[PDB]
Amino acid sequence: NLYFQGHMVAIPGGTFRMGGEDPDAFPEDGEGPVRTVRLSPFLIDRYAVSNRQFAAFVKATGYVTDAERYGWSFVFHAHVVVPEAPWWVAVPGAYWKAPEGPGSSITDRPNHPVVHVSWNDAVAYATWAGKRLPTEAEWEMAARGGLDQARYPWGNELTPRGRHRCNIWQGTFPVHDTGEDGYTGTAPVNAFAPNGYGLYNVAGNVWEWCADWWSADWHATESPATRIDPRGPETGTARVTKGGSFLCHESYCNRYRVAARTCNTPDSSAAHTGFRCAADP
Ligand SMILES: [Ca+2]
Ligand SMILES: [Ca+2]
Image (cartoon, rainbow, N blue to C red; front, side, top):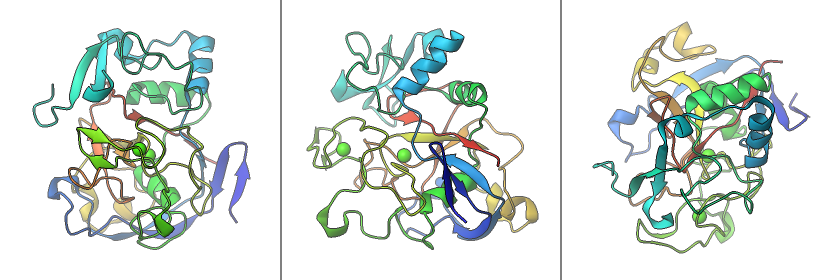
């Protein structure tokens, strides 16, 4: 049975339907096919890793993030470019402690998700914590919270009863975020309601690094490797991220549905991407 341990939830072994058939999904994202996947029991963080947690890691180890080694990271234009996504600016000195670059800080965001962390940085933290990154299937089973093929962690309605359940964009992207959900940037890792397994902000807030190499179609075939504790392709060039972010909106990406997925190279980082850890029982 489901139980809690520290700030993690112990998800029992089980079977669920992964993926989606949203009619507007981008073919290259490989959200389909919908497929039945059986997982062994695992533990997963109920919260994405926070600024204060990452700061404790850096204080204990002296870890220097990829964004600090490169000297820049990606910041959203409005908080002071990639041709296909011109709202993303490469900002020298943007990093986890200064998420909008020079002049910014995290003093007023101690319990927000840490951002500007690459996949390498996430793995470094997880390893120091005695943990690991979730597989994409573990992430999605946990984020679905026991519901079968719902659009979002809590069901099919984005705002049940008109109440916000996650931190995404409202308004007109990218020129005006109305902040109707309470936040025009990240929110605390423990904001909004939990899902059915106790996880917070699986949808929205920040994209979350997973263990798997990205593919659009490795998982399309039916086989034990793709359906029983699937770990993704053996190689790749980008790692999977899940969940969507405070910037996501139906008018451009529509990537805050639980089946959604994207990827980034493992040394890359951005103001809307963090991670949560997992562990084996
Ligand atoms: Ca928001
Ligand atoms: Ca998320």
